[PDB]
Amino acid sequence: GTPHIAILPSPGMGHLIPMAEFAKRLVHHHNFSITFVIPTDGPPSSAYQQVLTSLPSSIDHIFLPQVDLTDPRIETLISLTVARSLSSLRTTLSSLQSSKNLVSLVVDLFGTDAFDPAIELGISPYIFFPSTAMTLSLFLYMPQLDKSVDLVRIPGCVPVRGSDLFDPVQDRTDEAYKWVIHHSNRYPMAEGVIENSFMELEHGALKYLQTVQSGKPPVYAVGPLIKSGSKIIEWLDDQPVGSVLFVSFGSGGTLSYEQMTELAHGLESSQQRFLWVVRSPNQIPNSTYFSVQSQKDPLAYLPEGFLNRTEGRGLVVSNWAPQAQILSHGSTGGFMSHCGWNSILESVVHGVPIIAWPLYAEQKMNSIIVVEDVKVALRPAGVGERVVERSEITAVVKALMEGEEGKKVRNRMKELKEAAARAVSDDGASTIAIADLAQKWRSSM
């Protein structure tokens, strides 16, 4: 027979997408088969179902019986979902073992309680980390930091403000914090750690994590792991090479009504071409909310006349655009993003320079990698701390698209894109890491 791997993902497109791309990359050039075994505390989203049902026939999926959590933070909820699913998980993995050559279970950072059924059944427990090597190093370091505590010195990383540490540790009194410590202390139970990053992006963190140390699991750098819109592409086709700022704000959080108003003026005043994926703002004044034609229309909250005045150089679309296809298009010269790691890696693989717009603490850590460390990104003044003024938005858009700063960032991003292409080549570090994992799983047969 041939090897079978179970993968236990978190809820949320952000965790599922890179695990799905890992699974696709493994079965593409290996005769392996995979089951996604999905713990749930409620119905999965249609976007989550869309990813699962679109995978190749070598990759199936099973939902575990829903846990009733009736009684806030998503990490506490994930942790309780997995802990209350362990009986179901053991019986499911046993049933999989009777139809397939199950050799391993791969879990996320908040899935360490699922190690118990894996170890019980004699299959290898592995961790898959879909975010940065910097976040992995911070996760591993949390037990030490907890016993210690002015800038936070994450091993291998550029120093980081306490106020920037990923959101599950931003309140120590919270259950989410005690769960991060619980999972961090269990990390060495893993036979290996699969990291969604590559050396030229995070040399410091990966060098640290890959330092051979007795009783610490090996870390496999497998990144970058990345992947109806015809009218959007037809628009892009009609713009000159390198001219369009893609404002990819369809995911990664919500702007305030105030911030959305400043962003519309700042884009218009730049006179640059843009493709803006808009979601409904929050923080909406009563007078606005009750006066728009449709509450569901994100475009209804834009300034009076903005869409009419910009219609020659700006395409504004509701909620979605084909992000990978846009970033591949020669007309795309910039990418403004909330700096989800998946979004950053897409922009890197296509060589599109970034404007960093982080809203959440983990996005702020990601934005430090691209702005301050590898410098393939510019950031508007104040972003993540305060409303960004229209003049600050105009300034950063001009800097990226026409300025000397833009030219430098664009050259550095081209060199990083070439390093990413090398990493995923036949003889590249990510391909070698996937082959290494394949050989580990085959040896368990």
Image: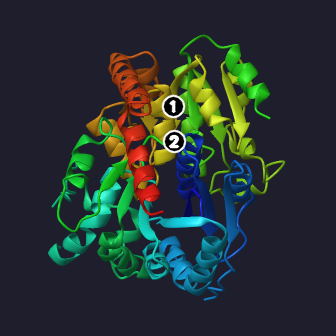
Residue where numbered disc 2 is placed: 343
Mark 2 Cα-neighbour bin, 10 Å: few <14, some 14–19, many ≥20: many
> From the viewer's perspective, is residue 132 above or below residue 238?
below
Left or right, 199 with respect to 269, comes to: left
Residue at x 63%, y 69% (from the top left corner): 38
Label 2, secondary structure: give it.
helix
Of all residues shown, which one is farthest toward the right?
293
Residue at position x 36%, y 28% in the image: 419
Q: Which numbered marker is on residue 141?
A: none
Residue 10 visible in image:
no
Where does residue 269 sit, x and y in percent of width and height?
A: 54, 24
Q: Which corner quadrant holds the N terminus? A: bottom right
Viewer-closest of 342 and 409: 342
- Residue type pointed to by label 1: Phe
Please tell me which of labels 1 and 2 falls first in the chain.
1
The three-letter code of the residue at mark 2 reads: Ser
Q: Are dots 1 and 2 in contact, CB under 8 Å? A: yes
Give the image location of residue 206, x and y in percent. Answer: 27, 48
> Please, is residue 145 above or below residue 289 in the view?
below
**Label 1 belongs to which residue?**
335
Q: How is the image coloured?
A: rainbow
Image position, residue 363 (x, y; %): 43, 51
